[PDB]
Length: 341
Ligand code: NI
Image 1: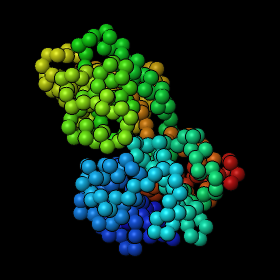
Image 2: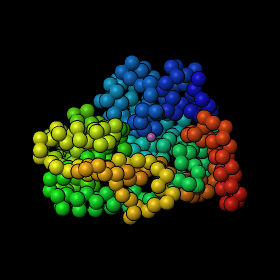
Image 3: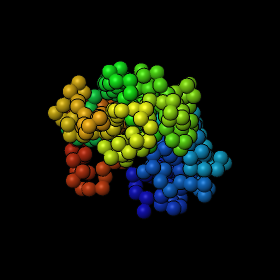
Image 4: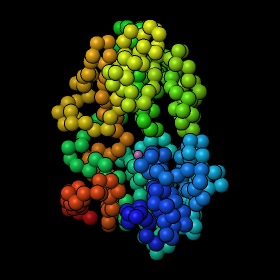
């Protein structure tokens, strides 16, 4: 059954709760972003109100074929009324179209649901700074102090410099980038830009990207693989077999592949800097794992929570084992005691 951490008390609202059939007493289904664990269950057959951002609404319509009448897009940073309750959508700094949701309850309680987020100091000067938040439904993906990672800017710098060097040494080298969902478009876009190429991809993926309101996107992407030297492929195909295979396809136009796998966290994070990353090589194929995260580090999460000073925290991630729940609850208490709320 729908877990309690997907229900907003004192409302008929749910968040990211599309795979339980009808939820008894839900009058409006919010969707934080277009990732499959969150939208799982949506389709052209859904006949309840879906509230989401404009971008998420483009993807519901074009990729899942949900009917227009049930999609209710809201503008960000704007006080809106939904079934008699005031709500605001904020940028979550996750994937395109991803939001946090502020609920202002009739009784006077204020609730923030982060969806999936990468906390940032910029959030401390949004509409969140304007009143007190009592309850926090928190993206706890990386809630443990071993999870450090570099900034997104440092990671893109590394990838741009690596690719440019490689292709300038060898003009017959192909760059390949893995993907399995929206998000992390900066990786392949920044590399394509330094190389003066558009990025080439399947028709399905091009259609996905054409829903995201990215400025000047027609200038940046294409479905003509021939005219492109940055290819996107399913992440599953980013391995030596899959890459040799792909190279055969290109008809001797390339003699070398340099591939990127944008991982979340991986345990070489606890010993190695970005400056000191190296690839896995087999012949004329090299594969870089780069730690580009769209979720909060442990320290970014800790800062955000210590700034917000919520009265109660409800985790939405890693909730399925008692050992994880108990460990999270310990950190919440440490933070609270250190900061004095
Ligand atoms: Ni996500």
